[PDB]
Length: 278
Ligand SMILES: [Zn+2]
Image 1 (tube, protein in one colour):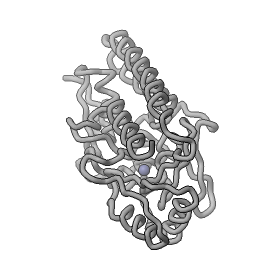
Image 2 (tube, protein in one colour):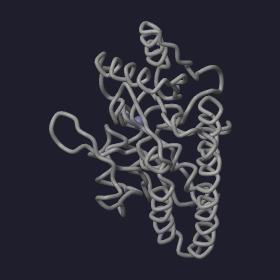
Image 3 (cartoon, rainbow, N blue to C red):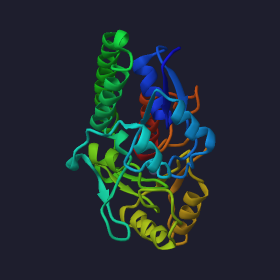
């Protein structure tokens, strides 16, 4: 009986709950901990999309391998974004868009709005209720932005350099006067160029960076092979991977862990950076 809303990533899974609460029935396609860049829609998945009353996804080719299915049946929460909002890099000609918009709280608040207006119009009777829920979460995102700022303000200008497995924090860095390096491009669907590894090594050396970060969606070996190369130039920069020491880029944490919800996933990321960068 409850409306069925298919949802690509754990990100959206959280958002909708935050907004619609228990009023709708959520169909998460990509399990937390998996990588949407590579996810390939299986029969069951396409089925979920088909059976869905509403389908919500990021867009910007984030899902990477379901554009020709989501664009057909679903609504990208990034439909309202404008050109200047976008981050754009280069890759074999073109002007490739950076999908990791959610670390730009403003952009995420935008997404939240689209999601709200789609759950409203899906539940006419719960529209005001949802709008009320939306406002409360918008404000929580507001408070969050202030939290991150105050939290980051403890990291020295010279230490404002983030190193991650791939380019997924451009929107983040842009929001808080940060510089991001990554041995990989915007998508994770490509071989780790050994020339970008070195590029990164030299960047670490240039800026005397003593901490490179690890993420839950990719193999941390890459960052340990990156650490080894640095030391090969002596060279010595810690790898933040340990246990529970992972940044979330392309996914939240499994319900329910510390990176459970979006705002918590955010705080987790932030605290982690300050600890090894401050
Ligand atoms: Zn990514």
